[PDB]
Length: 302
Ligand SMILES: [Ca+2]
Image (cartoon, rainbow, N blue to C red; front, side, top):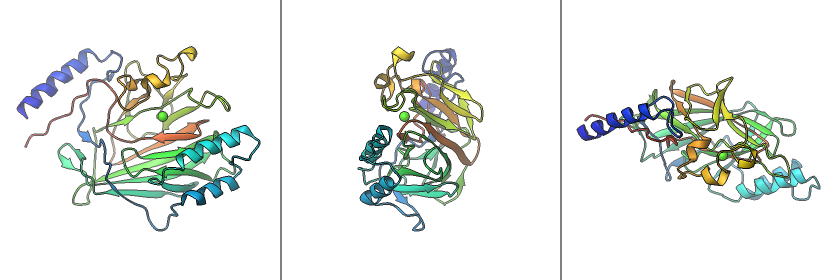
């Protein structure tokens, strides 16, 4: 402890003098939240909510006009994207109805803590707010077995906006307030769309009820309604990217800060909106694995 504190102090001094450097947090912070990975979480969804079978969802999506036999290339490409994500049956397959919340509860958490206190349960509430798809009242999403991998959702190359509420609970089942915790909003691609629809696909986070901390040099900027996304392509150097997608957009890439922003938690119920334009399939991971360089973990005194 007394040596981790030394080290953490020295790392904050270093984050301060390098804060204007690429990859560094523009305002130095330490991490007190540990919500990094929970591969063996127990996932529970109320029996109220239909969890689709693979072929059952496939037939539903086809009945919506999104099928391989639609002569409209944009529709059939939306199908092959949907089909790909529909092939993993470890996800819970959900049909969101506009304005109707869906809770996804993960218990049996083995790795997570905040400032020394064990996190034993995380609850996600998903509510479709808007889609450019069909009558605008429905969208597919896929809840991960792992709460830190979190979700895929679709837009079928239109647009989707889904509100997410997140609540963390300790071993006593009491609501926890993760104020000061850092969350990783990562992999917010712009310009990585399908060349058959439009290259300027956009992934964003909107309406975050916490405070963003810009990563220096990152393509992800703050906009109105507390929203974070890139202002131009972060996918192709020929459209002005620093790095092509493949050179930064992985969980271990040393350049992954390029598509990320940090979120500082301010409330016990965390809230943001996942929103996409022209993406087809969208991965949205919610966790504490900060992409910024040199963010120290805050040690806890026994
Ligand atoms: Ca992404």
